[PDB]
Image 1 (cartoon, rainbow, N blue to C red):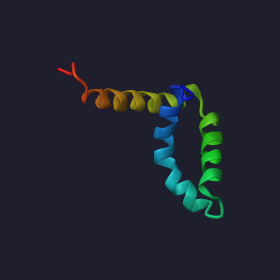
Image 2 (cartoon, helix red, strand yellow):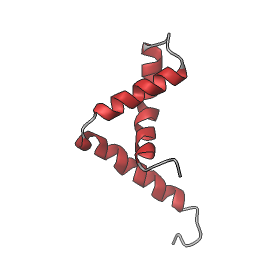
Image 3 (spheres, rainbow, N blue to C red):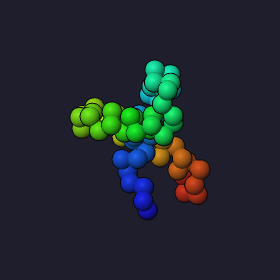
Image 4 (cartoon, helix red, strand yellow):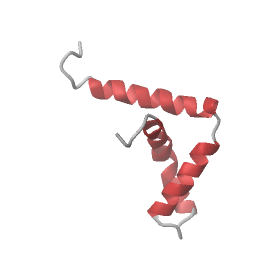
Length: 71
């Protein structure tokens, strides 16, 4: 609804990068770290974002293995 396809790719990128960013900027709280992750994500080129979108799609497909109709 409010969530669009970029968010799932961004969340892959964030899961990878948040822990080290939090430790490197430990005076910042989680909400501020989240803002910094979003700015870093938006500086990536379309080509750089591609593998995160590709991985988000693989994750989606793996989730759909739970559904009736898988195999």
